[PDB]
Length: 343
Ligand SMILES: O=C(/C=C/C=C/c1ccc2c(c1)OCO2)N1CCCCC1
Ligand SMILES: *[C@@H]1O[C@H](CO)[C@@H](O)[C@H](O)[C@H]1NC(C)=O
Image 1 (cartoon, rainbow, N blue to C red):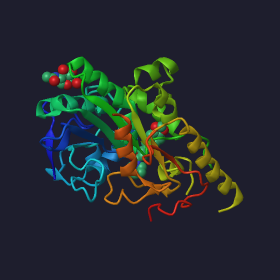
Image 2: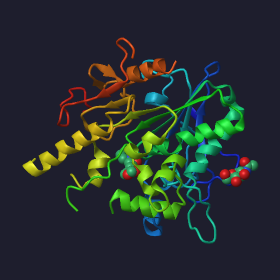
Image 3: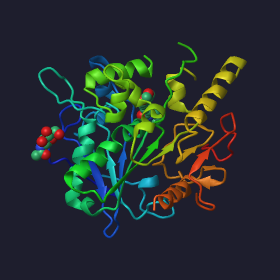
Image 4: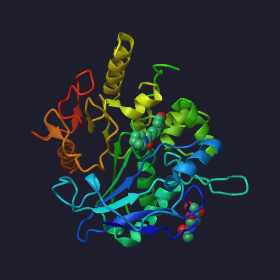
């Protein structure tokens, strides 16, 4: 089990002003650290954040969090369930800021809610340095769904923070799961581009510096889209993305005749195209919302290679490799054309 620690700097808060936190299981002797960002959509104005507070309060507040959680999938400490990093130090960071991990704004007389996702990540890293992270060789910042987009937004800032604090030997890397979205046309027609544009203003959202300098003021929403922000990043990032992701289809208003068949096939081709120049990637031809912290994450294969194997080959590459591939993108054009897709 992973044990809850609420942040000692109680000014770094969840949406409602309660302290943010992290769950930790230490592994003495290991110099690998895995920090995982939870997902769960977002909210972008007073009215829709008020609704989220009524029926999704654990995503806005720490008041009801449990004292422990069980690590599963890539967060499991059992080699049978996690062939990749079962002996690592494990950290689960709850998503309680509703801002795709981008915010830097406190609750005040002008702000009903605090949006502090970017500061939560920084404060967790700072407090872990005194709990063993100072001795790390690799820090892998991972995350699923909104947490996967959060990895893309924050991995280079973690690297810069550790350099400025005097720890240049820790190698910072990212693993973005299910957070690589397209700003495409909907099948029928608040779209993500508009909702994110409003969210950035409401959250005081921040984006990576090189991407910000390309797109400039008013256009920072572009940096929330993986294919646009990825080429600006300096840290190594492994991208996991279903070709027919259910959250992508939801925002596209897809819930089969010729028009819809062509729409779905074109979506898969577009996603494949955006990954052509991403050297470390795993993209199966499945319709799914399943994520890498699920217990059976080992079961899916692309071209005969599982995700835990691909991640191990990635580790070796950062020391091509015979029989140890890292670029695994399906080419078949319809969901479940890969027989290993989740049931
Ligand atoms: O958190 C999510 C999905 C969140 C999607 C977040 C998101 C959607 C569109 C975007 C974006 C981020 O930036 C670029 O455009 N879940 C979906 C399925 C599993 C439950 C959680
Ligand atoms: C607490 O966090 C806030 C926001 O990141 C920061 O301004 C302040 O310096 C922090 N204080 C300490 C003692 O870490």
